[PDB]
Length: 163
Ligand SMILES: NC(=O)c1ccc[n+]([C@@H]2O[C@H](COP(=O)([O-])OP(=O)(O)OC[C@H]3O[C@@H](n4cnc5c(N)ncnc54)[C@H](OP(=O)(O)O)[C@@H]3O)[C@@H](O)[C@H]2O)c1
Ligand SMILES: CCc1nc(N)nc(N)c1OCCCNc1ccccc1N1CCC(C(=O)O)CC1
Image 1 (cartoon, rainbow, N blue to C red):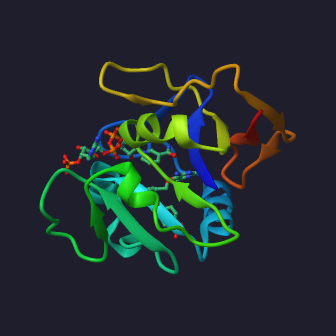
Image 2 (image 1 turned 120 degrees about the vertical axis):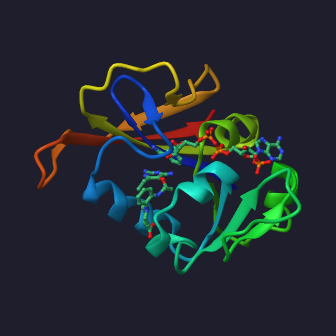
């Protein structure tokens, strides 16, 4: 089982200036609950984007997809392709692909699940933004209710499964 998990603005932005252009504690907790104890696979730019306190993601096996021989920043297992990242795999549990846009594009054809947090923050897409992948007719989804964060932003979760 391969799942993609991401947070996006309503406009579809996932990344800007090497980071995430909002702060949503409730999404961080959701992401931690879904991924704890599992393998997380990410692109190398996302690895380098993590705040140092959070790299590697504690309690998870951190796999980083790169074309380089290895990385200066410690704590990852490097692989040269998504296929190498995914096999061997943890039994009875998802491997989670946690970004960014390039790695989501590689993983989308292989995935069985997508877990999306939508953040109602007004962020018109800018030229260099990383955007969320678009889901085609092979996906069926359900959506939770709109929630209000302690910081005032409205957000909600969408969950998709391959038909
Ligand atoms: N909102 C969210 O949920 C979320 C989640 C994660 C990240 N983000 C944001 O997304 C942005 C980063 O995304 P991104 O698309 O620029 O980068 P990315 O997917 O994180 O990483 C791209 C890197 O992955 C490696 N790579 C890509 N294709 C490969 C392939 N076929 N084989 C081997 N290695 C390959 C390359 O590493 P090398 O250059 O080392 O070869 C490439 O530079 C940041 O803004 C980050 O904050 C947002
Ligand atoms: C939460 C962002 C997010 N949200 C959904 N829904 N999906 C994703 N793929 C995703 O990006 C994860 C990679 C970037 N994380 C990240 C980026 C910037 C600051 C902090 C973090 N971290 C959050 C998770 C914390 C942990 O889990 O311990 C540690 C700090």
